[PDB]
Amino acid sequence: RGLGTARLQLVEFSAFVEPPQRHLFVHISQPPLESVDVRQIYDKFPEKKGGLRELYDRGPPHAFFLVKFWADLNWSGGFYGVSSQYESLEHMTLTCSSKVCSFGKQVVEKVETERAQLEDGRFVYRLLRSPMCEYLVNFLHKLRQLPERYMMNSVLENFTILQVVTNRDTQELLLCTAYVFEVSTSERGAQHHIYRLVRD
């Protein structure tokens, strides 16, 4: 079990800031996964069209994952970027939609397209150094100034991301990942915990 199906697998995901080498706010580099019932987090995502509940209803359910991040927020200019890499055995073009939610309502949607590239006997899909939406750069700047880690976590309870990767040519849903967030201490460092989303 990783974040992936037989059809597409997440290889690496990071959100970072670079000076004008890198600070990683969160990072995934890729036993069986534990499960989280989607009803547990229904009250953290839009009940609106295209949200988590509507998508999970249409399935397929094994495409759905939850990532809990403990972000490192201890690092004024600079490049804010997000990098993601997927791999598959079949040649596809991917549409990747990233939806930022604050208090349930969607405040950002970012849609990118990536064509397969053959590498080492498989297909890779590289969306590297995508600039972070301005909403998030400003939010990180404000969040960083909070005096106490528990105040950051309070604020972050209301903040979620939903990423939806689809086969662009077929419109088939390949992967749907819900992200929730807390802040880590500088001593522990960034951490994550991937879960299968279930409902049965």
Image (spheres, helix red, strand yellow):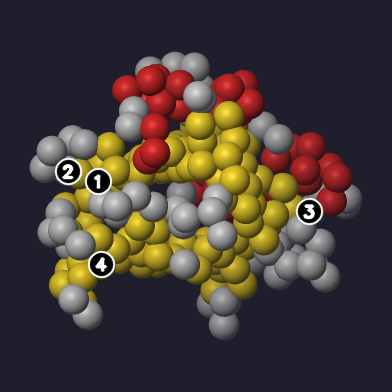
**Residues at marks 1 and 2 touching, judged by CB atoms closer than 8 Å:** yes
Q: Read off the residue under disc 4.
A: 124
- What x and y, as percent, mark residue 29? 50, 68
Residue placed most toward the observer, 8 or 177: 8
Dot 4: within a 10 Å radius of its alpha carbon, few (fewer than 14), some, or many (20 or more) residues?
A: many
Up the image or down, 162 lies above or below 82; here it is above
Of the numbered discs 3 and 1, the one sitting upstream in the chain is 1
Disc assigned to residue 95:
1
Up the image or down, 48 lies above or below 66; here it is above
Residue placed most toward the observer, 107 or 36: 36
Q: Residue at x 29, y 52 (%)?
A: 6
Of marks 1 and 4, the one in the foreground: 4
Report helix, strand or loop for mark 3.
Answer: loop
Alpha carbon separation for disc pair 4 and 3: 38 Å
Q: Which residue type carries mark 1?
A: Thr
Q: Residue at x 59, y 68 (%)?
A: 24
Alpha carbon separation for disc pair 3 and 2: 40 Å
Q: Residue at x 79, y 67 (%)?
A: 188
Report helix, strand or loop for mark 1.
Answer: strand
- What x and y, as percent, mark residue 2? 46, 57
Disc assigned to residue 145:
3
Of the numbered discs 1 and 4, the one sitting upstream in the chain is 1
Alpha carbon separation for disc pair 4 and 2: 15 Å
**Residues at marks 1 and 4 touching, judged by CB atoms closer than 8 Å:** no
Q: Residue at x 20, y 62 (%)?
A: 89
Disc assigned to residue 168:
2
The quadrant in which residue 10 appears is bottom left
Q: Which residue type carries mark 2?
A: Arg
